[PDB]
Length: 26
Image 1 (cartoon, rainbow, N blue to C red):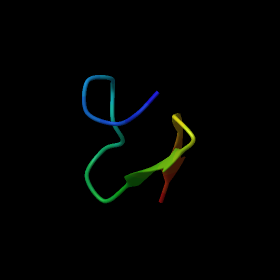
Image 2: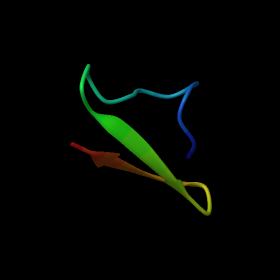
Image 3: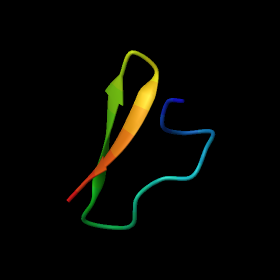
Image 4: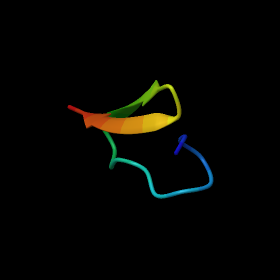
């Protein structure tokens, strides 16, 4: 899923959207 409606990474970390997928990056 995408970022926003669902959980998200903590301060300092950023998520990555890939064809609907979501990967947590430092």
